[PDB]
Length: 103
Length: 104
Image (cartoon, rainbow over all chains, first blue to last red; front, side, top):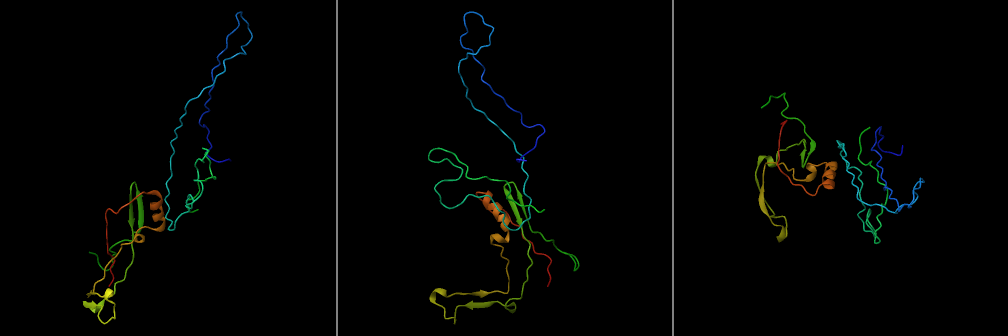
């Protein structure tokens, strides 16, 4: 209901964890669980590649369609860009429904 | 060659987009009068009171001619939209012309 593709078998959850690295243990054995660890974290790169199939528009409509367009007029910023502080923003929601089809 | 009762061509107005090619086809119905009562005529700016810049000399002909040289003769407005929103350029490649279903 929030929109998109209902899947019986969706893309799987991908789970990641830093492996615990104990700190120095005591010199005599204790059966108590280790509470003492070397503080650490991890970083890397992730890539996602998705192939999408397209359904082409077959229309015989004579007159021009409504299209999504950026405003041609001047402004202080460009839509869907960073500002002078480096903050990327999205000016508005963009749906998918522009082209038309007979009912 | 066809008889009196057979059509010599079919109506084709279409636009086909394939790869880097688009093929436009347009069919129109035309009417041709007799011009100049079948005569060639010398025509001129003489006795028109024309300025020097507007003078001319030439001939009018009994003939008519076909002119398809404009873009809306070929692209529909929607087709023109598809062209200009999606493409950095375009050029004409080849041409096919047909006259048919003549009635005098």
